[PDB]
Image (cartoon, rainbow over all chains, first blue to last red; front, top):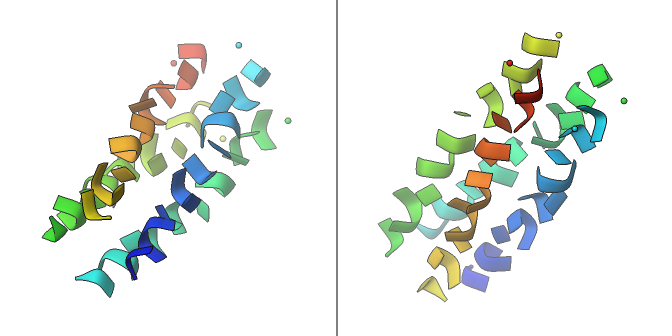
Amino acid sequence: XMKXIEDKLXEIXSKXYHXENELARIKXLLX
Amino acid sequence: XMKXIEDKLXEIXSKXYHXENELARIKXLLX
Amino acid sequence: XMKXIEDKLXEIXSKXYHXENELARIKXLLX
Amino acid sequence: XMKXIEDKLXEIXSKXYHXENELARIKXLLX
C-alpha cells in the first residue's frame, strides 16, 4: 500500500532524472 | 481511495512511457 | 490529506496534458 | 508517511516547473 505508493513516487522522481537529462540530450543537439 | 491513488500513479507510470518515447520522436527528427 | 493527495495527482494528470501537447508544439516546429 | 508522500508530490509539482520551462528553452531555440 503506502510503502507501493511511496517507492512509485522512487520511479517517478527516476523518470523525472531521465525527463531532465534526456531534455538537456535535445537542448545538446540544438544549444 | 488508496487503490484511485495507486492505479493514478498506472496513468503516470503510461504518460511517463508516452514522456520517454514521444522525447526519443524528437531526438528521431534531430539524432 | 488523502483527497490533497488525489486532487495533486488532478494537477499532474493537467501538467502531464500541457507534457503531451506543448512535445506535440515541438514535434509542429520540427514533423 | 502521508506528509513524505505529499511533500514528494512538492518535488513533482518543482520538476513538472523545470518540465514546462526547460520545453519552453527548446521551443526559444526552435519558436
